[PDB]
Image (cartoon, coloured by chain):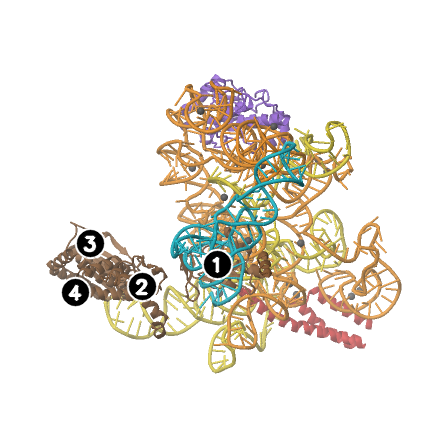
Chain colours: A brown, B purple, C red, D yellow, E orange, F cyan
Amino acid sequence: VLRESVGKSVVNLIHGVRDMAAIRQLKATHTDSVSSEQVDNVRRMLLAMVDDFRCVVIKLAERIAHLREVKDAPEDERVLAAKECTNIYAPLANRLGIGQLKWELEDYCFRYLHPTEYKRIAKLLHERRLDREHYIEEFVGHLRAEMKAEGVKAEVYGRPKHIYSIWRKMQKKNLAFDELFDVRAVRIVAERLQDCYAALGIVHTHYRHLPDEFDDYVANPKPNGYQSIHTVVLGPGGKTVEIQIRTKQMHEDAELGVAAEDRVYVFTPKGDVVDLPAGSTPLDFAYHIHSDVGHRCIGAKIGGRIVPFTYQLQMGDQIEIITQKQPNPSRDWLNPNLGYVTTSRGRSKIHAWFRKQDRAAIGGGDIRLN
Amino acid sequence: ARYLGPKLKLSRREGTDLFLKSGVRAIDTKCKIEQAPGQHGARKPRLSDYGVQLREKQKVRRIYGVLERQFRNYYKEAARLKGNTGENLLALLEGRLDNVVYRMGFGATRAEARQLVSHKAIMVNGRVVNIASYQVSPNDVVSIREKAKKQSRVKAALELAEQREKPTWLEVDAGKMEGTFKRKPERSDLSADINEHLIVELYSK
Amino acid sequence: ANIKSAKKRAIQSEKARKHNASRRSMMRTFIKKVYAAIEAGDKAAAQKAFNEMQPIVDRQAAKGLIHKNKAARHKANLTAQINKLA
RNA sequence: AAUUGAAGAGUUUGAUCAUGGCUCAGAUUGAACGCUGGCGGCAGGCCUAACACAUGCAAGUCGAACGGUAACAGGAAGAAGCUUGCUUCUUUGCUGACGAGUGGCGGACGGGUGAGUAAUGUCUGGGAAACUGCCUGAUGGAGGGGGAUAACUACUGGAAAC
RNA sequence: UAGCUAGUAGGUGGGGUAACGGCUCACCUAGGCGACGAUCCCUAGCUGGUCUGAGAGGAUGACCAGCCACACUGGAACUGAGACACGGUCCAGACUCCUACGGGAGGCAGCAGUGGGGAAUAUUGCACAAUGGGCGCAAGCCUGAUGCAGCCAUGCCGCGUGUAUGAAGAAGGCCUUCGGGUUGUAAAGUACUUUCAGCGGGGAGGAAGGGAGUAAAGUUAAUACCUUUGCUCAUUGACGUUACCCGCAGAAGAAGCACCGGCUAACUCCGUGCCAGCAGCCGCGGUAAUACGGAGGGUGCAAGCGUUAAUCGGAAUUACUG
RNA sequence: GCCCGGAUAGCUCAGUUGGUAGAGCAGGGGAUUGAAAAUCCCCGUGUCCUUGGUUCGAUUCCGAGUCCGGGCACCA
Ligand SMILES: [Mg+2]
Ligand SMILES: [Mg+2]
Ligand SMILES: [Mg+2]
Ligand SMILES: [Mg+2]
Ligand SMILES: [Mg+2]
Ligand SMILES: [Mg+2]
Ligand SMILES: [Mg+2]
Ligand SMILES: [Mg+2]
Ligand SMILES: [Mg+2]
Ligand SMILES: [Mg+2]
Ligand SMILES: [Mg+2]
Ligand SMILES: [Mg+2]
Ligand SMILES: [Mg+2]
Ligand SMILES: [Mg+2]
Ligand SMILES: [Mg+2]
Ligand SMILES: [Mg+2]
């Protein structure tokens, strides 16, 4: 009825969110437990849901609203769905490049997974809030001035670190952690790639770059699509100063990613997915589609390029079948040693054709007698 | 390419000493040279004419360490060449670089010589030769390079050679570990037990 | 025609063909006048025709349309015929 | 100096010699299948369907043949926010060059296959009635007129092909 | 397959061709081919060669090279020096594709590749660096020619898989006249070496040309420009972690297939029972099988070995030699 | 994808919503020959496709997976 009133996409989306909240043990321990642990989500039938990215996006906004609410109430399952969200949804969001939603998720999770460290690094952040904010507005001041004077225009601002990521840096830098330097971050968001390179040069004229801490993620984008320049200069009172230069478009993609302790699911020209067993061939696929097609199946294309009939189909890759007008299956297809048909059904179908072309006795006799 | 196995078994099968072991300690004491190899060694076989020829062929092949195809090729070459065919074949076999080395006394056995050749120990006219089958022509000097001179194995081989008979067609120096191939070895130089004619016949049937 | 060159050649050929046909056809017509005259039995007329056409034939030969030898041949035959006539 | 090359065997019979077939021992391959299986070098690799063909590439080049500039990099005349010095936006084949075109030469070579052909074939040998771009050697000309035509432009017929 | 053939054989003249010619037409003569095989049928590219063979022959024609023919089938011409043109044109046909249904497009027997057929034959690789070709005055661009690379033991050839020593003739394996004798100096142990493989380094040759500057000579009114000849200057590598050399560690990672009655090299020991199986031929197997299956032992070859197919050989068994 | 049918001595087949399985040939074993054929005797000589269920008891009935034989649907 969703499908009748809001098309096949919206029902696919509703059904994927229902899958990966797997109410299975959402109620079922009712402390939300298969919201939590996939426990093989609805099995590997996670790997028979719809891949449409709006699944993960409505799942993430759903869980984010929930973590807001899991500041307030039910106590110990504040604990449960926080462990799910650390271990699953925050690093999912991150390997999608939805950094905004990773950092909110992580801060909610961490503040009811370890309240002592959440509270201790929160309080520490106040203790040097002023020397930090003053030194950020002096750095942003100098940069705003010299660059504006040189005829370049961009946003230049400080950005707080988020509590989970301070914690993170504090125990991969213990006793060389600096509450000041390590919690400053200048960002520059420029109009053009041109202006990113320009702001890089002017920054480097004002304050000397440190050797080995200059890192061009615009030239080499990270796997979740993250692009910026990073540089650490040596600022006027901060023997490191961290600076992230990018365009607007690359800030939008960096904060908002994708939104900008058996079987093989093969796509088809349109998109209607076909399910074969693991180790299947083009021939098998063809047969599945239609036995007549299989009979008349000349050549197998995969993603544009031609493939050998013997080569097995990988999961997800898109197929095309070049076809004749007459049906002509080879007797070689039946023979399993060549590696043409892994499926039984397909083989049977193939066989049938030959028998048709061709066009007990005792039992019959007995019957007659009777 | 080579026979990786019991050296003296072959000798036993043949009957005669093939020189497949150095000769520090004698062949008669090492193995039961009189008896043929296997369970039915004492059973003396009534050997056919073809059989005898085959045996002869084997013996020669064994002696040099020349497998069948190679041997055949050599025979063909000999035939192509002018004069006595068997003699030519024999000469060719001798001319094998490893064989030459062995004769000189840098290999105790021919196998050893072959190994040395393989392992870039030997040089011909100031040029390294990896290949055991290399035909050493007249007036071609053959030596060991300075990196392989310091081996005790070589010394041992030399000693063995000294103990044994000297070839006429070769000249050799013990201290320098080098020598000279003067001319092609005649039939009188080689051993008289090798009936080359039989071998020739066998490659005419 | 898969290759640009072929296409060009093809159109050029068509154009060339049209051109040559016109010239060749004209030449043929001219020849026929002479031949016609010969058939009739009018010697002066025939001669006149020959005069009219021979130069054209020569020109054509020069151009390449008709081969030099071919051009010569027509003249020879025509010359022979006219001689025979008178 | 340049073919210096020629082996038999088993099996007809109670046994023999002979005729006589079948048959094995050799060499060989564009080979395949089987069991294996380290490497190198040099070679070879749809013999059958001259059966069907998706995809890319396999013949283009010449701007020093010619009008032209469809992208580009330079100058040239003008001007915009004027960092007192040129970044920049407009125009013009003026130039390096070049889309598309006309023209030239090349697409008749190179590559493929062996279907057809027992001779408008091939091999060898002889010929006479021939043409032969570029390359070539020689001897003489290259004067002076035309009208076209793409290209490019408007209005249009076609889904496209055109 | 004994008769065949009317443009058929020849002639005169016309026409045509680049050229001679029934090449084609008009008219005439009635021939021409043929049992030295015409005709018709079947098969077939042909040659250099290849294999085999003592030769003579026989078989054969992948690769490389020459010549011919063909380019989805059947035509036809056009252009051109040259084609009746693989990646040109025109038409028809069958066959795939596109189409707004009116009409279009297409042609791997180019190189890759896919399907199919098959017993069976490779990667949609890189490059023009060379050699050759195209164009151009050149630079240059194109070149699936070519050069190289990948895959497959398909072949040939080479090389390796350790070398020397080593009796307790160890153990285990198999036989066994029960003593051993065989595996077998084989292994282990000891010494010695490092082919190729592995790592790290170095490191030619295939590269001759071309480009700028110059100086001289050859041209011309002219020391310009152009061409020719010298010279320095930086250059030009697809293959390419190239060939090739060195150092490191350590036997380390590198033996298998057939055969074993006679032919035919190599033999002993079971189950069974004319069964199962073997087999190239003769023939083995009907309760003691050197022939079947295994084990050991051997023999042959060896990174191959066998089987099968196919040819010559042997087969003087088409004999020309003979 | 779905259904229906079939899967029993060596091998032909017989027996079914439930009572420990036969007919032919083949095979055995004896007499008998060297062994046979003939002749003469005597003899089932079986994983009912495997694994579970139902039952007082399963070849059979229900699953569950296999295998084969259909007959149906499917056009990326
Ligand atoms: Mg097949
Ligand atoms: Mg070899
Ligand atoms: Mg005439
Ligand atoms: Mg294999
Ligand atoms: Mg151009
Ligand atoms: Mg005539
Ligand atoms: Mg043919
Ligand atoms: Mg002969
Ligand atoms: Mg044609
Ligand atoms: Mg012409
Ligand atoms: Mg083509
Ligand atoms: Mg023992
Ligand atoms: Mg090496
Ligand atoms: Mg024997
Ligand atoms: Mg056998
Ligand atoms: Mg003969």
Q: Which mark is residue A19?
A: 2
Question: Is residue A362 or residue D128 the one in the foreground?
Answer: A362
Q: Quarter-wise, where is residue C31 in the image?
A: bottom right
Measured in 3D between alpha carbons, the distance from the residue under mark 1 to the one under mark 2, in whole angstroms, is 31 Å
Measured in 3D between alpha carbons, the distance from the residue under mark 1 to the one under mark 4, in whole angstroms, is 56 Å
The residue beneath circle 3 is A169
**Is the CB of mark 3 within 8 Å of ligand 13?**
no
Image-based side of B24 in relation to E49, left or right: left
Q: Position of residue E115 (x, y in %)?
A: 53, 57
Give the amino acid at mark 4: Asp
Q: Which mark is residue A345?
A: 1
Q: Quarter-wise, where is residue E254 in the image?
A: top left
Q: Position of residue A302 (x, y in %)?
A: 45, 60
Measured in 3D between alpha carbons, the distance from the residue under mark 2 to the one under mark 4, in whole angstroms, is 26 Å
Query: Of the residues under marks 1 and 4, which one precedes in the sequence?
Result: 4
Residue appearing at x 69%, y 65% in the figure: C68
Measured in 3D between alpha carbons, the distance from the residue under mark 3 to the one under mark 4, in whole angstroms, is 28 Å
Question: Crowding at label 4, few (<14), some or many (≥20) Cα neighbours within 10 Å?
Answer: few
Q: Are marks 1 and 2 on the same chain?
A: yes
